[PDB]
Structures are given as C-alpha cells and as structure tokens.
Amino acid sequence: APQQINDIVHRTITPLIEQQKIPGMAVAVIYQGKPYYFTWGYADIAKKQPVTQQTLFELGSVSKTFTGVLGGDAIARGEIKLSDPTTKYWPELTAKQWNGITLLHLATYTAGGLPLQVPDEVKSSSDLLRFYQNWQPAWAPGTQRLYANSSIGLFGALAVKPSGLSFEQAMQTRVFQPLKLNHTWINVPPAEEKNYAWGYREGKAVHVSPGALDAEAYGVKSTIEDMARWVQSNLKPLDINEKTLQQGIQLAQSRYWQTGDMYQGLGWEMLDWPVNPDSIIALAARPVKAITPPTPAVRASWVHKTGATGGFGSYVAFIPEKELGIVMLANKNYPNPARVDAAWQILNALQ
C-alpha cells in the first residue's frame, strides 16, 4: 500500500488490537476507489490459524445492510412498496395493532417498539406469527425509533415473498452473485470451514447460534475482500450493471427519518459529512422526525453500520463524495466507540 495508508492503518489498528485484546483482525481501506488490505493475529487461536484475506468473519448486524439493499432491489423490481401495509405480505397477521404499520416502519425500526431480539423460544413459522400477533406496541407507528432485529428481520422475510425465493436464495441470486461476493455466506459451506474464524467471548471460541430471522438480521459471514467489494458497490452504485440492484443500493442510502444528527436508511445509517466524530445502551428509544419525502442518497455523507455477534465485532464506514471507505472485521465483540474512533482516525487522515 502507499506508505500514507500503511502508516495510518498500522499506527491506529495495532494499539487498538493491544488495548482491546482482539485475537484477530482484518481491515480494508478503499482509497480513490481501490482496496488495500491488512491482517493481524489469529482466526483460530488453538489451531494457530492466522487471519488472512480469505478468513470469514461473522458480520453480525452489518448483515442488515445486505437486507436493506435486497429490500431496495425488491422495491426497484416492483415486487414490494415500502408504503405497503405489512398485512399485504402476511395476511395472517390479523391483530389490530398492525393496522397502519408499513414495510417502511419495519425496515427502519419505527413500527412502535418491536423488540431488539426475537425470543429464543420462537422457532417455527407458527411461533413467529404468534410472536408478532401478541406483540403490543408502546407507540404509534412512525413516531419513535428502537433498533430491533425483530423489525428489520421481518422486513427482510416479507420483502422476498413475492419473489418466490427463500431469503437466502434471493440474497445469493440478487445481491451476492451480481456483485461477485463469492465468499459471502448466510450458511458457511463445509468446503469453506477451513477459513471460518472462531469468535472469542470471555476467552471461549464461539460461533453465532441459529435463531429466528437470523439470516435477515445478523447472519452473514464474509471475507475482508468481499466486504471491500461491498463498500465499493455502495460507494459507486452507478457502476453496477444490474439495474434494480443499482437502484436498491441507492434506496438503502436514502434518508427516511432523522434522530439528532443521524438519518436512518435501509440497514445503512448516515450523517452529513463532515461529521463531528463525537456525533458518531441495551435499549435506546428516540423520537424520529419523518423526512417527507426521503432524501435520495447524499454523496456528502458518513455512511456506516456497526455489527456484533457474541464473538465478533465489525464496522463499515464510507464517504461517497470522497470515494473513501473502511471495513474493520474482528473476532471479538469490542466496544463500538473504539471502532468508530479508529475508523475516523484513518478516514480523516486520508480524506
């Protein structure tokens, strides 16, 4: 890499790894559109396997960016509309609280307090229906944001219904394959296990457990190379040949709601750039202001998403107007502020 990139990345990341006791980490910097890769430490401590550019990490909630884009693609295809009632795609959802809750609300965590987690006890399709039928909103739709797997997770599941495909099949065919993300998986195949890092939680090697709506909310695994390509694709959607996918990416970066300095997209979250680094809790309820109509993707944005599983911590941030971005994948779930601080140090130095 150019020495400037080499130096700021190493001088930022090495101390981070030391301070947070991160076993293994991969970083990609996208600079003037080109990717530069860095790796440290161990994918598997016990087996002494190093992190490489082919190592798979659990993205955790960074998966929601894929879900948002897949949903965007389904909108572009005319298969769904964000203004559609949820009940249009799940008629069995007959309980009265669902009147007025749209796909937009599900996608953007504004349905009225859907909970962060789908309970472990919810497994079958019948269990899932029961759960949503019994849920009692605390708030009217479109008034408060509460970040929630059960919200965007349901959005993802419903968004693919008209397609006839499973969520996984839709994601593969419509998102992963066209973008050549050939080492990105909802379910890691046996052939790829050699490259699947272990996560570390309290010193124990762990992988994400199966759960309802896992694929949709937190279940993607990917390499640093594929994630760099994901950032490139989101930085420059116009280079994407597939029309509805190009559109879907644009829709996911539209600004639907504002809370403080942040704007909610589909999966992605955005702030105006330049962004006060200080501007970038188990449950955090915030009133939202509707952006009527949503602002199309603003190039002068800090666009980002954090993600965690029990054993992994991921972060992606990019600035379209600067053709600049970063992916940080680690096999420990370390504090979000440390992720953002490191990303900002690096991108600020390069912009």
Image: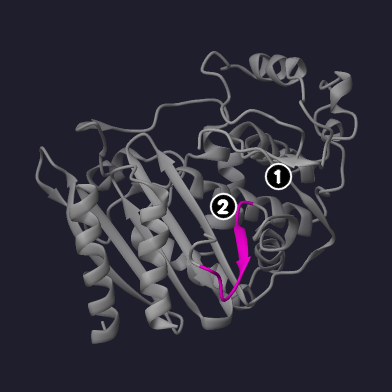
Mark 1 lies on residue? 107
What amino acid is at disc 2? Phe
Quarter of the figure with the N terminus: bottom left
Q: Is residue 269 magenta?
A: yes
Residue for point 50% across, 40% down: 218
Question: Which residue: 80% across, 31% down?
Answer: 139
**Seen in the image, is 246 located left or right of residue 101?**
left
Q: Secondary structure at mark 1?
A: helix
Answer yes or no: is residue 109 visible: yes
| Residues rendered magenta in the picture | 267-276
- Work out whether residue 274 or residue 218 is closer to the camera in this orientation and state it: 274
Looking at the image, which is closer to me, 72 or 293?
293
N-terminal of the pair, mark 1 or mark 2, is 2
Residue 248: image quadrant is: bottom right
Q: Which disc is residue 21 wearing?
A: none
Residue 193: x and y in percent read 27, 41
Colour theme? one colour
- Which type of secondary structure does the marked residue at label 2 adopt? helix
Q: Main secondary structure of the magenta part?
A: loop
Q: Label 1 sits on what residue type?
A: Ala
Q: Is residue 111 magenta?
A: no
- Provide the residue designation for mark 2: 66
